Image (cartoon, rainbow over all chains, first blue to last red; front, top):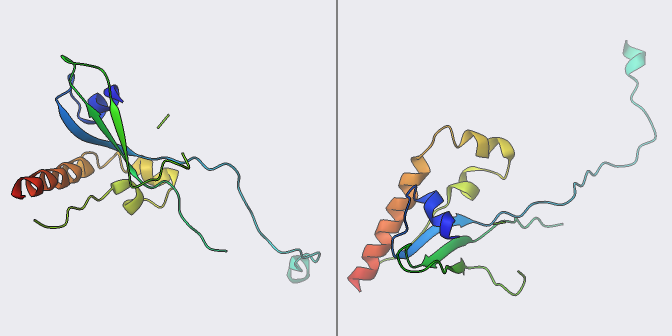
Length: 48
Length: 38
Length: 49
């Protein structure tokens, strides 16, 4: 976080004070796909 | 089910400069730290 | 004095997608100007007190 001051301000040194840097990044874990249970396929071969 | 979004709050650093000290105090603004950058 | 606010460009512009964060860097320092402008308000609001 000393070098996060140098990354955001694009400067080689650090000046004395309070600086706003960045925000939180929460990585997601899993993926949820929800579709109802239908055992019937669509009649695409009837029209073709 | 309700949807409550994630990744909220800022990161603020408090440090003296490079001619003084390398110690950095980090301020988490608006986020309670009892529940809890690489 | 007045109400001191700060607006992030990450959560406001993007809907947490990987395509929006990659195309934000092509516009560059447009959100670098806005975060330094809201910082310079909040320094001068503490000098009014």
